[PDB]
């Protein structure tokens, strides 16, 4: 009774964890928890996803993830199911299911409601439930808690309930998840103490307590709001630097040497647009609007970042005209299609906006992303990607790096110089190449341009 | 003879000779720091009162430790002053820190800068180094200052060094920051950049961050104030959003800022009662106007300025609303505004957001008493149209509200148990810029106060 909702971490028998949702977040969580000794079962409605995990397969490009899935599924500590039945035997249940938003920027509770309606009858006294899915504030306590209580139990008294925002760093997720402190917002002191004991023992990280689940839900929304609004500042700064003939990355690097606030001045890097950062700031805006608060910094940031794909296409076409090129003699090789660097997800990518604007004007575009699924590129771009990097760049008049994947940095530009059509423009969207690499491109005959570079 | 370096070898026995044009806040902080490390400095200013003060070892600038440093160095003879620009000829380095105010259209008023350059230009000799530190619109150093300095026959970069090095001092801790902050150097060429870097490293003992041009360094200064002002806007809107959920914005900011991001961490700034001073209310508009002239729209600046300009009025509306919810009216409540300065731990009220809060409260029918022991009483009369209270007891005795609109360290050290016996019960404690932790809020309630803040 003194230590509710979690066994002593020193117990010989392993901790039993059920993770609802076997997406990017769920898989990273499952692998890192199983790796530290817990017995984990990932629950997902997709039979294909469950079949892959059970056979130690993972198609996610996240570094070290496919290897860890294959190793842990073989040790038996990582398993998967389409059924929510393993919830009954679990000590901890983590909910990472999808929470999208409609055109009005209001939560689509469907997936979360369905997951909660499956967990509720299987929920047992003494269990700990943690919500990781990004949600509108008040959701854990006013929507999720009554759904979980439909099975007769009471949150905080019979089972622990806490909101812990997901803050995974793509491309380095497995490394960051083992060091990054977890924010815990308990639905009461018992739920707060148990959620903190769980992350410290099962994950081995520090914990940052906030006084309610609503406070922790706002931490997630405030983080995405801060990131989106700071990317908007950086994007506008890059367009200002471009008209002055100054390099935005030197400006940002020098500006960020000033201590300020809780750490340093932190101008974020500009890009080709934003693709968490397009829904969560609007989610806070709609919540604010319904409560009589206008979030003007969110409205402006979204308008600024939504204009960047069209501006990127305009800059590419303008630079090609300056090189004496046109839509009749140039094929553009778009290298990298994913919304974020070192990911393969193209579901909500600003690259779609760049390609559409380049095609809408009349340019021939080839797409290549070594991390993305070719069927997903067909679905989102409407065309099959190039068979390989060599096929994409051969005879291309422009190499537009619109996602800065690590394998693009390891490319031999001397070898690329022999495949492309001279004069070739290297447009740097998300590579953010250092001056030493830009000199190498010029040496091989490439023209180089970035927004504000 | 060989092409010349634009700075003498710091191995020479004679002290470095520096001339600082513009002995205001930035100029005086530089002068005492350079002279304190051994350089011989002459402060050149158009105000005869400032020149007379520096000569006598006096300084009217309230900046902590500044008057003391001036007194010590005037006695050594290393720091002197002049209304005349005749010391320029003998100097190794000329630093320009004159005022660059903007007009109603946010265009820079070049009057002081042109007058300074015109006096410097014919006294310049080959091999000298000229550093511009005043905040300017990009391209000012190369297209305005350089041709004015060349009127004597010298050619910038070939005959003398010209660099832009922005000042990044924060008011109240300027003397501590001038000796620690890395200096950004934007030379008009490689020789100017090398000399300016060697100058800051050897004469100030600080690190240097080179940027490729004077224009790049001019943008660094404007991008910094743009970033700060826009991030205060995010924080103020976040506090207003937290207020409707009843969540504490300081818990949210603290937890959010534990995430590594960019080149450091997520850095949500602290909310307040608005934004004052020249830096954050003028510099982002200067960038906006320069961008507009060149066909670039800075929408984040427009929104940040609108958001922060609305904060004083919103703060007064919150105080008035919380007083009504407490059962207090305009008839039985005198509000004591504690802290008038634009910033915590300074006395500067020249452009303070507290002015807007006080004016909006009075326009709601409330009597307001002002108390700020760090501020000049005459400065409060000129900005607020009323004399501040003689003492803390006069301000708080019988007050129905204690509105902490500047969070000076002095206010954190008050005896709230004693205050509780002087105020009119029930007394509202409004936290504008104290940012009290939950333990301190609990203590106020135990003493009988009603604590409120935006998003607290
Ligand atoms: N105030 C700050 O904290 C701060 C911080 C960073 C940057 N800056 C920039 O530094 C510059 C100076 O700021 P400040 O607050 O010290 O200014 P200030 O207006 O208070 O002082 C300027 C001084 O220059 C003198 N002066 C004017 N024209 C002159 C001339 N032709 N010859 C000689 N002296 C002349 C004036 O008499 C005055 O004493 C501004 O461009 C400002 O943007 C200020
Ligand atoms: C840094 C900072 C400044 N401000 C406001 C107070 C001052 O009026 C103005 C300038 O502050 P600064 O000189 O400390 O940057 O901006 C905030 O409200 N929150 C903050 O976090
Ligand atoms: Na609260």
Image (spheres, coloured by chain):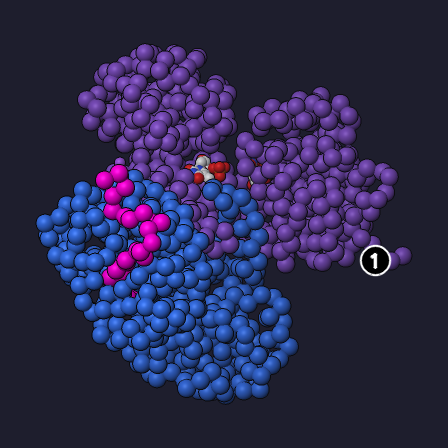
Chain colours: A blue, B purple
Let me know if residue A16 is in the magenta part: yes
Q: Ligand 2 is found in which quarter of the picture?
A: top left
Q: Is residue B86 left or right of residue A106?
A: right
Residue B13 position (above or below residue B63): below
Q: Where on the picture, by quarter, is residue B298?
A: bottom left
Q: Chain of mark 1?
A: B
Residue B131 position (above or below residue B41): below
Q: Is residue B438 left or right of residue A290?
A: right
Percent of width and height locating residue B215: 60, 55
Q: Nearer the viewer, residue B318 or A122?
A: A122
Query: Would you say residue B431 is visible in this rendering?
Result: no
Query: Would you say residue B422 is visible in this rendering?
Result: yes
Q: Is residue A277 left or right of residue A268?
A: left
Residue under the image location 77 percent in, 57 percent down: B158
Q: Nearer the viewer, residue B71 or B249?
A: B249
Percent of width and height locating residue A227: 39, 54
Quarter placement of the N terminus of chain A: top left
Let me know if residue B166 is in the magenta part: no
Which region is colored magenta? A1-23
Q: Where on the picture, by quarter, is residue A410?
A: bottom right
Percent of width and height locating residue A355: 38, 76
Percent of width and height locating residue B370: 39, 20
Q: Where on the picture, by quarter, is residue B326?
A: top left
Which residue is labeled 1 in the image?
Answer: B3
At mark 1, the secondary structure is loop
Residue under the image location 74 percent in, 44 percent down: B202
Mark 1 surroundings within 10 Å by alpha-carbon count, few (fewer than 14), some (14 through 19), many (20 or more): few
Residue under the image location 29 percent in, 23 percent down: B445
Residue A308 position (above or below residue B140): below
Residue under the image location 66 percent in, 47 percent down: B207
């Amino acid at each position: 009774n003194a230590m509710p909702f979690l066994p002593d971490p020193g117990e010989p028998s392993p901790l039993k964890v059920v993770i609802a949702g076997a997406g990017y977040v769920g898989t990273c969580l499952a692998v890192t928890l199983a790796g530290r000794g817990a017995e984990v079962v990932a629950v997902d409605s997709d039979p294909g996803t469950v079949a892959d995990l059970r056979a130690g397969r993972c198609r996610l490009p996240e570094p070290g993830l496919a290897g860890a899935v294959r190793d842990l599924a073989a040790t038996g500590r990582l398993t998967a199911s389409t059924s929510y039945d393993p919830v009954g035997a679990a000590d901890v249940v983590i909910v990472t299911v999808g929470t999208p938003t409609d055109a009005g920027h209001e939560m689509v509770t469907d997936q979360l409601v369905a997951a909660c309606e499956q967990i509720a009858p299987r929920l047992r006294a003494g269990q700990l439930v943690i919500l990781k899915s990004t949600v509108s504030p008040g959701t854990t306590r006013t929507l999720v808690a009554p759904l979980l209580e439909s099975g007769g139990l009471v949150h905080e008294r019979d089972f622990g309930l806490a909101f812990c925002p997901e803050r995974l760093a793509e491309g380095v997720a497995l490394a960051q998840v083992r060091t990054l402190p977890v924010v815990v917002g308990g639905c009461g002191p018992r739920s707060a103490a148990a959620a903190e004991r769980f992350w410290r023992s099962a994950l081995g990280v520090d914990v940052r307590q906030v006084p309610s689940a609503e406070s922790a839900e706002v931490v997630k929304l405030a983080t995405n709001w801060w990131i989106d609004a700071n990317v908007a500042i950086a994007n506008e700064l890059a367009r200002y630097c471009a008209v002055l003939g100054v390099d935005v990355l030197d400006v940002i690097g020098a500006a960020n040497t000033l201590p300020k606030g809780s750490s340093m001045v932190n101008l974020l890097l500009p890009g080709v647009g934003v693709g968490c950062l397009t829904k969560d700031p609007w989610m806070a805006w709609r919540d604010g609007r319904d409560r009589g608060v206008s979030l003007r910094t969110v409205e402006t940031a979204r308008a600024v970042n939504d204009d960047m794909p069209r501006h990127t296409a305009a800059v590419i076409a303008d630079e090609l005209v300056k090189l004496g090129r046109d839509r009749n003699d140039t094929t553009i090789a778009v290298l990298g299609a994913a919304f974020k660097n070192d990911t393969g997800d193209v579901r909500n990518t600003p690259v779609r906006g760049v390609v559409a604007a380049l095609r809408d004007s009349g340019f021939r575009v080839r797409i290549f992303d070594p991390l993305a699924d070719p069927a997903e590129i067909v679905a989102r771009f409407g065309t099959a990607p190039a068979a390989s990097l060599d096929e994409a760049v051969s005879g291309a008049g422009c190499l537009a790096f619109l996602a800065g994947h690590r394998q693009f940095h390891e490319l031999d530009f001397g070898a690329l110089a022999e495949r492309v059509d001279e004069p070739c423009l290297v447009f740097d969207g998300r590579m953010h190449l250092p001056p030493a690499r830009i000199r190498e491109l010029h040496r091989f005959g490439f023209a180089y341009r970035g927004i504000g570079r």
